[PDB]
Amino acid sequence: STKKTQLQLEHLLLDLQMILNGINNYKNPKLTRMLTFKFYMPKKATELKHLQCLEEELKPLEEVLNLAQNFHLRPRDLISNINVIVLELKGFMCEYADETATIVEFLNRWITFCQSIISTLT
Image (cartoon, rainbow, N blue to C red; front, top):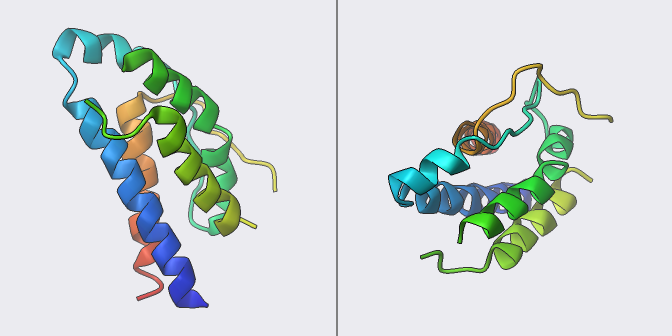
């Protein structure tokens, strides 16, 4: 059971890295515009339940990705896969930090979240 959970988190981790890697490959003028969009961050993220904070930001994430545009998956598909994993993992009202972050900082934070939880299940 713990193994199934770890594997789901690992897939979420790779999914998030794929978005970040794709975004890092945008041309700079484009990336500069993309970095103006505000994302909301969890005050605290240490347990699966905290994934609610990620779930609520999936819509704006998909919108921004759609607005952007070589991605080997359509944003709707990529976000759908992330959506499924998040829904199955968190099975609480998300507390957000005052400061917003760019899409890059937001992805990093959630990538870090996954890596941290994965390491408690090894």
